[PDB]
Image: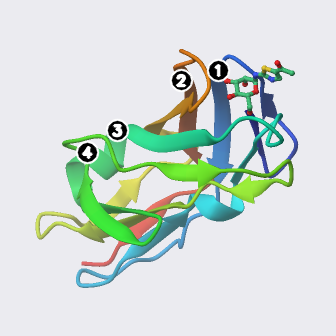
Amino acid sequence: FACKTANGTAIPIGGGSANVYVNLAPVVNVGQNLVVDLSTQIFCHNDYPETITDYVTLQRGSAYGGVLSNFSGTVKYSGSSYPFPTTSETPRVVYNSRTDKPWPVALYLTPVSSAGGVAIKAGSLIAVLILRQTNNYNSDDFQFVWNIYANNDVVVPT
Ligand SMILES: CC(=O)c1cnc(N[C@H]2O[C@H](CO)[C@@H](O)[C@H](O)[C@@H]2O)s1
């Protein structure tokens, strides 16, 4: 089991970490969601689906910088909504194919009422997402750590 970003940056068998740079809606009104769809940015696959079934969760999701101070967050993992920053490990998604399959995570970030002005700075770390991979075959328990960075400023109008 291993993962890659949309630009080919890989985290190999055994886990590790990678940077993910995301374009963000430059203007987000109070009452609207800023959507960070990681399903188009992170892809994983099973290296031995002939024998092994891989299990994949979002173990933890943390917010940083302007996302932590200016937004109220929800994470969707495989269609189910949870608080972000996260309070528990998600249920497992099965990876049973060698074909790249999106990691089904998306952040929905709505501005808090105190938000206004440049709410997310360009180049800043906005989130760290820990993917945890196990299987039905051995004791492998690996972390794939995704550091999410904003490619641009995001303003909440005042
Ligand atoms: C041939 C053989 O024994 C193995 C091949 N790959 C192995 N193991 C690798 O691939 C598995 C399936 O994605 C993962 O469950 C493991 O965690 C590891 O990434 S063992």
Q: Which residue is mark 4?
A: 86
- The image shows residue 65 at horizontal and vertical percentages of 34, 40
Give the amino acid type for the residue marked by disc 3 in the picture. Answer: Tyr
Asked which secondary structure carries label 2, the reply is strand
Front-most of residues 92 and 154:
92
Asked which secondary structure carries label 1, the reply is loop
Alpha-carbon span between mark 1 and mark 3: 22 Å
Q: Residues within 10 Å of mark 1 (few under 14, many from 20)?
A: some
Residue 15's disc is: 1
- Looking at the image, tell me whether mark 4 or mark 1 is earlier in sequence order: 1
| Mark in the foreground, 4 or 3 | 4
Q: Which residue is mark 3?
A: 64
| Mark in the foreground, 3 or 2 | 2
Alpha-carbon span between mark 2 and mark 4: 16 Å
Q: Residues within 10 Å of mark 3 (few under 14, many from 20)?
A: some
Report the image quarter containing ligand 1: top right
| Mark in the foreground, 4 or 1 | 1
Alpha-carbon span between mark 4 and mark 1: 21 Å
Alpha-carbon span between mark 1 and mark 2: 5 Å
